[PDB]
Length: 74
Length: 74
Image (cartoon, rainbow over all chains, first blue to last red):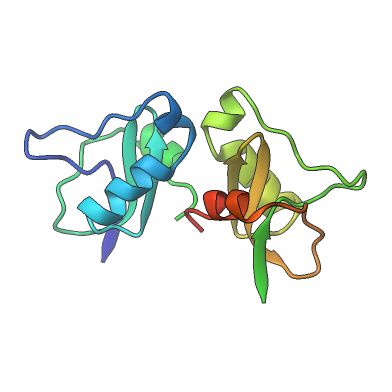
């Protein structure tokens, strides 16, 4: 089963996105698909949020309010 | 067959999106799904762009550069 969330890098941190990369999904969509092999992604509250990540991919912890807000588009 | 594009309203115009509704997909996603019965949507260059619109839904004309840029997420 796949999942959605903020993928973490080797330093245990999320991928920041701001400015033009916060308004357009392209930057985060590229990171999500090419680096974490997810189905898609966009910038959700300052960090790249991905959809369709494989279950083994480490993602950042988040409150229910944040998760519900970020899950959109797939 | 479904299609993607800028749905037009009764006045033959697109749905404008700016400010917080240009940074977050929620506004346009709601319009796209609830008003035009599409699968999803987001703000692409100042207007709500929808995915999965039924073929009979009138959409705004756009150049190839704009279409390729907007098609992301589905």
